Length: 276
Length: 100
Length: 9
Image 1: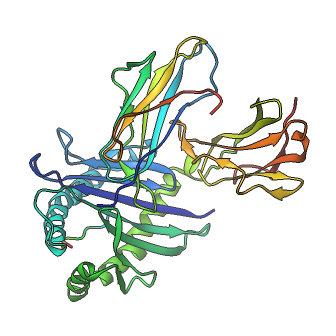
Image 2 (image 1 turned 120 degrees about the horizontal axis):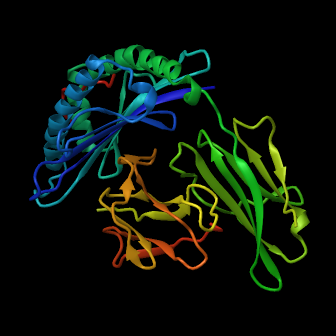
Image 3 (image 1 turned 135 degrees about the vertical axis):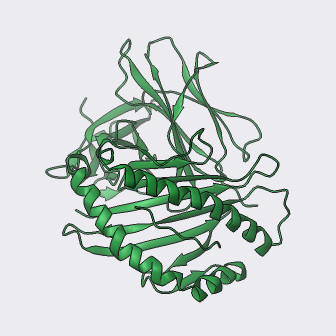
């Protein structure tokens, strides 16, 4: 199927408690493979998945250098952003960047991504053309003009279409036994009486990878969108994910309800009912 | 400034089986800013040395973290997660329920 | 490899 490589940068100022912490994590789809933390006793890009461990010293040294430079650049960016919003030196602020590329089943580039946020709100983003910017406000227009003058977008296009995709394809091959393996959900329906006239039906999906899944309830073949309680898909800690969907049903009407499951790992979509 | 309060889920890695070692998870998500305090509790007491994932975030910029520790579920032992964040006046406690 | 942006915001 399709795949992505994404890096997630978070820098957080903490006035009075030293300089802003910088964290970078890298993912291939839902699998983290590297981390860097400027607050670690000895900051270094570290492996977080077994398949990346084979990379040689140059990979670890170069990514550590990029991260150490980023720790400093993001602090300069936070100082600039504070001024662009006329903010006091007393408050804490956050700068985030997420960037990377997507490829299809043939390994060809689908699109690149580069987006940034300040205090959790969209600030500036590279457009899908990898050539122009979208700035959220007059502060981001200052960044945009600065990056336009230095032709940053052309540099980002070259990275996203070159290095980005070359390394995503390399990771997909080195980790193919996991990264290109879809594990289907293990499913079951539970029944929990609430009162004499209603019960909860809960549809479970466990042990699946990747996280994308469709889990719905139907009543007489009609989707129960508004009436379904659907928890966020959550990590189990063994690379897999979990999710459930529940509906409150009238006593005796359980057989009118069907749970539908769609996932890449399944040979066919599932239709489940409560089995007393 | 605009802030987002955490969603909280408490659950086990594997299906719960009384007397079988497993992992107790507390997944916090949807929050901004990233500073957050999470404790795992056994019978109301803080479990020591709980580990957590590396800070990352979702497409809408909100953060997520997984806190986890070994635990052996039983009929009588109570497990929970306690979360504090700038958006909360008091720590929020979510009890572990094997049905959720 | 990661990208490297030396120019601040």
